[PDB]
Length: 259
Ligand SMILES: C[C@@H](O)[C@@H](C(=O)O)[C@H]1C[C@H](SCCNC=N)C(C(=O)O)=N1
Ligand code: NA
Ligand code: NA
Ligand code: NA
Ligand code: NA
Ligand code: NA
Ligand code: NA
Ligand code: NA
Ligand code: NA
Ligand code: NA
Ligand code: NA
Ligand code: NA
Ligand code: NA
Ligand code: NA
Ligand code: NA
Ligand code: NA
Ligand SMILES: [Zn+2]
Ligand SMILES: [Zn+2]
Image 1: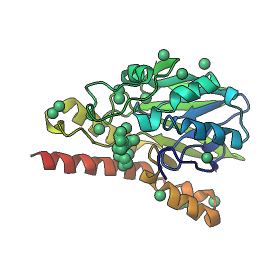
Image 2: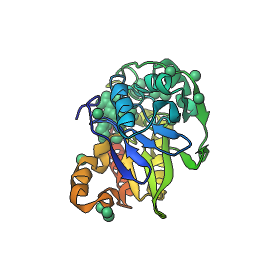
Image 3: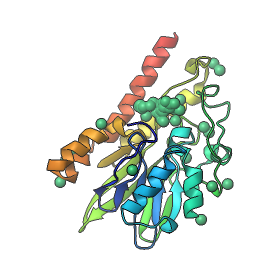
């Protein structure tokens, strides 16, 4: 389950399909009027994601938007390639637009000094907190969830099967990780941003959570459960609370370690 590994795609609920790699989530939200892709995975992973979209019966040329959680190689490295293959517009939080364009994270990033660059994308545009992305019948909401990066966005929508609907959340990373030379205790904006983000995420309507790193909400255990239980195995309306709690615990452990 490396970041760039093949992974047979699968439908999670309704028109929400997992098209990511073995290690990094990417989601296609489909419609007859075109599709939205969330994240690109790695540069090498773009070829996996593209093949997976086609394996689900969809055309790349019908992907109209690519939504970015945040601008690190593991989630965004494949966006540039996907953008070329699709012609889509890339949407991101304001403070991550320049990073997506260039593929270089800035000095404000806690991991600056330790990150690998990734390919810059074309057609990158900003969205604001609370903003709706509409495409035909699709409606995806942006929630600012800064901390891991300044422009991190968590994306939400509803998917339905014969009128039975669920609230789906593609949860951005909420993790306090850094270069060796970085002290969170010296950077109050980052700490405040992380804390605000745990609070936002634990309040979301959240039947089905798909974490950027899929194991964060036990995707693979859930998929194994689903073989017998069906797609209810993906449903757990405490998942966003649990992702937020794990974020909080990581930060609190880190601040304690810094004293
Ligand atoms: C560039 C880094 O951000 C990347 C790396 O290993 O290089 C990893 C580290 C953390 S934590 C990874 C697993 N998730 C834990 N909650 C992470 C993320 O939370 O998105 N990505
Ligand atoms: Na694959
Ligand atoms: Na591009
Ligand atoms: Na476009
Ligand atoms: Na973003
Ligand atoms: Na950034
Ligand atoms: Na960044
Ligand atoms: Na651009
Ligand atoms: Na971080
Ligand atoms: Na994470
Ligand atoms: Na520091
Ligand atoms: Na520093
Ligand atoms: Na798992
Ligand atoms: Na079921
Ligand atoms: Na269930
Ligand atoms: Na369940
Ligand atoms: Zn990251
Ligand atoms: Zn990551």
